[PDB]
Length: 124
Image (tube, rainbow, N blue to C red; front, side, top):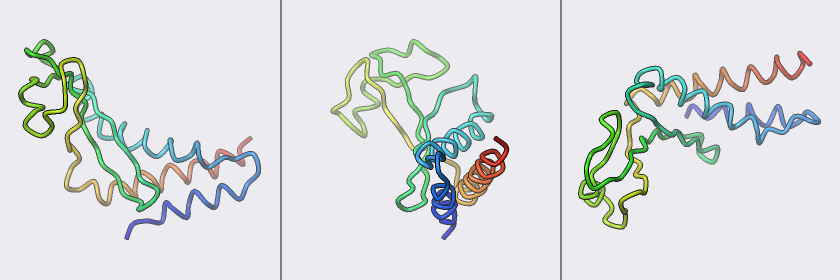
């Protein structure tokens, strides 16, 4: 379901000099950017697109520190241990922060991105 993007990229691959490998990066940058508008100066984030199952997952990257130093975004060393005690002060932790409506948005973002590569590629 909503895995049309998978075929969208392939269509571009058929073209010479148009590596679809780089196209996949466009979709991600789009989805992450779209959600970033919600909290850009509030906190960072890293989206990971999976062309294998046409799925998508948004995770927030927080700075693991013994004590909160960045009011904008930070995670207590003890907090990260709650889900992964393997963490350590100075590392980074990722937590699901994607909306429950991202399911449809994913295709809407990937469909709009792949489409741009088509009109753009022919553009020059």
